[PDB]
Length: 289
Length: 289
Ligand SMILES: Cc1cn([C@H]2C[C@H](O)[C@@H](CO)O2)c(=O)[nH]c1=O
Image 1: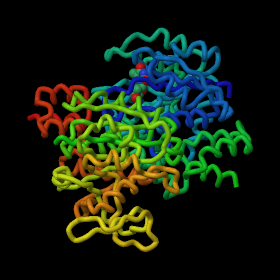
Image 2: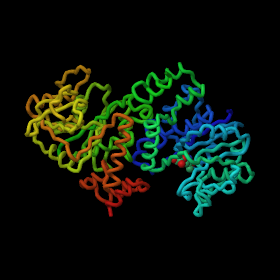
Image 3: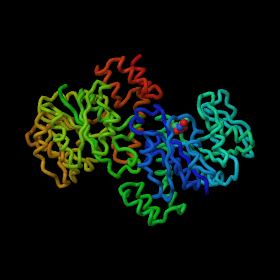
């Protein structure tokens, strides 16, 4: 698709200290791979090869060294900086030149998704010609998230950021698909009651035009909380369980790129040569033979 | 008390890629805290306030970033670089000026110990007037480690690396105490068949002089493998289980410094302020009240 992706990987906050004294949160391992691999692979599964990584002045070079320009994966990776964490909607203001007049998508750098049918779900969001698509996930504590109520036709009826006051149990997750209107909408967002340039404001605008579609991630879908140390440990336990007990690989960009045809097997084998020592590399070998 | 400590944190190796593409192995989080905190707190529990961190050219500034000079913990941290991974014994040549004519201790940057009687075990080793002390951990498969056989008085009689026939079930761990002879002893080590200046040669010299004592860590002690992604995850699970079920922290330098009297309660409250968000900081608050 001509859709282009943004990962917002900015300020984690002190919540994960002292672990995050060492590194920024989206570079911490979730099981065997850096956190940023999971939302990146989400964009890749949706078909986006053009990805803008937005991070802090201090951390952007660290991502640059980890990921490079993405040509090793048949991708084009670019970088821009958020000087202060003023809101998710700022991603489209920082990302205006990279987006051009293409449809776009935003995923948060600490959002980890899993689902057996997730790729058909992503591809379907990518196929909407217009409007916006958010992803709804059942949680037991909606007051901590953005909450949506929708018309069962996939049409949202209300959307509230951290309501006192919650109108449903469906949290809006950190994955958003948009047509060409979002940049101008984002530029017009005013700071919310909590002082933030909220993506919820963006989605409310789409909802008022009747252009907010909601994809449900119900039974079988995982959306991992990376907010706390305990929830980070749970995220690692989950990924390790899928890979060791069920023989599944989550968020391996080399595999996704090869199976998407963005690199060939010769390019893929070249990627494995410096990784031959451990199971991550031996998996890429097992998948080549 | 007058003893000075070294942490040797060497090359991560491709074994933990791609996670260690982002961060050095000894900066990976073990539950809520960077790995390096664990061997550090071990030196701290032994009473050492002066610690030299030896690492690779590429990784040494990262540790300085995380830890600073240690003055926040009433300590004095210094840094030197191992230019090439030519063996563990080099730490005593590199650290020769830091050591002076003092007793010393060496711990490997990836060694995580826990046991109810660990501090008394360390202090007893620290109290040795002369000679050297190694720390042996009871294993069910001694053939996989370097094995020490010792007399009924705690004096080492043999030390063999990966014995096809074990003379004991006690593996030598990466924690070593030495008198003032070690800097000179290390200088006399010849390169092994591994092309490295091995600590085993250092320990052999003390044993050849009949001055190698062995502390055994049996019932009640844990010694965690950090070699693989699976074992790293299990290490995190271990720490999280003990800390949440038993109301204790493993390798919390702030706590060790406060309880040892190296900082006062006002100083400790200052350190806690940036950690208020999580369970690590709120633990320190509970002990303040
Ligand atoms: C509000 C905000 C959050 N974030 C990131 C940090 C959080 O880990 C995550 C929120 O789930 O998104 C940014 O990168 N920039 C911002 O402006």
